[PDB]
Length: 32
Image (cartoon, rainbow, N blue to C red; front, top):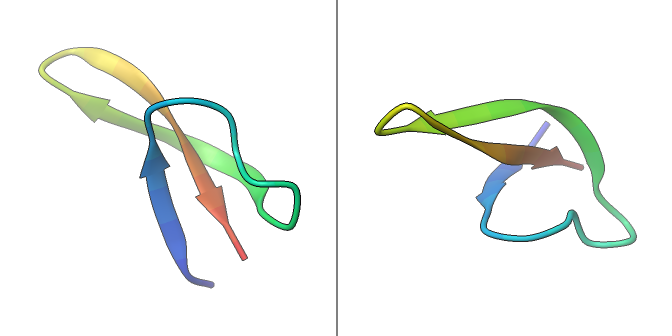
């Protein structure tokens, strides 16, 4: 799977797969 740590929501073709953590804040991990 190929993934992005996103600032907003996942793209429609991506699925939320986890969270990314940056400086103690959570972001969506979105994968395809």
